[PDB]
View 1 (cartoon, rainbow over the protein chains, first blue to last red):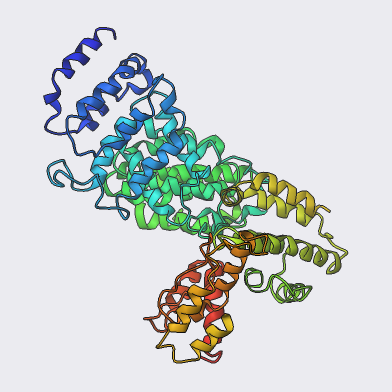
View 2: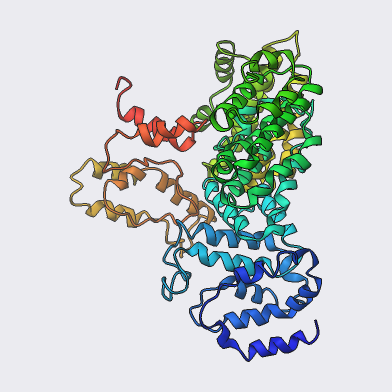
Length: 357
Length: 124
Length: 124
């Protein structure tokens, strides 16, 4: 840690290193993979490396990077504690910039010099590393990234509009699929642990009608805006954006944590809303885990068979699983599911006696 | 309710209760879901459309419509769930959707205290 | 003043001399520099200005941009709000296509439809 100030002075003597391209995304990822959890020494190093990297990047005059200068103007004194407190509203401005990158003030200060040599196929490419360097400042982010995002979602700041929300959804999806693993890893417990069992077991409320509210786009009015709905929306966003390698850990996840949480049937509809619409992404390249997902759902059946008196909307799940089998898996997982569906309820047997065939 | 409040906030002593009875009995008539719909109505406005004195008209219309539904519950039906527990689960369903009151606070800037005060006033 | 504005809009209107004359003349801009026995040359004056603005609004709209003597905070929220260079074949998209997914009445569209009905005919 201590003599690292000498290499800081050295890079100050080597500003020319950053006179060609600003692509520290990979240089932070590969050197931060297992570091965010144990960054304490690197945290104290960044305590002084913040201004060092800022000046190293400042070897230009397009006045394009403001979030760094915004932190600088917000870091006049005691830079170890203050600039990380009001981040949510700050993040608003952050996501604000992003929600202005696609439809807003397009000819802004961001695209310039020269739109084709600063690695500009799109302003989001520049959004990448600025978001990275912003969230790489402290250590409590990454764990706090998804938390603050969910906050600015439900604790909607007066700057966050409610009509063009889907742009913000795409924005959060991009910023999540851009940041490394210890940053988006919080979304698992953000969806399954926070609200998926808020009360949601037997006497939740008269809100039990699942279809009209649990699916998104129901909050088109100022009414019909449930927290579970916005949570599912944030989910689907991060699912579609990160549909490259982040989804690859999802099957085991469902087998690890989603088992002792499913109690009621609308919990089953919720986890279906979470998992289903992205299975074809696996089918494209990751077929080898589909069966897992399959039996995962099948395992859920067992639960919704034990602690359950009656099933009102069961036939939706029946035909859902039917087309799950016939359109995607086919005669592939027959032997594994044979030993698991034998424990179902008489109605489920009467529904899936052709599935077992 | 939206149209009536936006058109004539006055001169509406009790025709609106008549139209409410009409649309209720001449349709699926769940009293809890009924009051849920009417509450979502009287709060979906007052936030999006108005910007100035129209918001004052909106809050006045809400605080006139709540005695309307009150006397509706008093005179319409009596003998089976006399507008006591249905109102309970109605306000529970209301409390379920928190973004409603979130937008209410984003609009009125005091929707917590003002909400409690209008609640205890309607409890007259 | 509003009566004579009505007389001028019923007049040729191509002259517009007396129209702008009464507009700049009856303006509450001058806050009674002399000892005018008003005692409320700020509140009463602003209320008189917004009153003269409310009435004859669409009347002054018949001419070009008026001098705008109100200088308040927020103008009338509801208005004509109809695309002039556009036919009435718009409720399909601006109204019906929205409410197809919009499970409400959208008070803006409420006033739009209300104005559209009396400007047309219930049959068509």
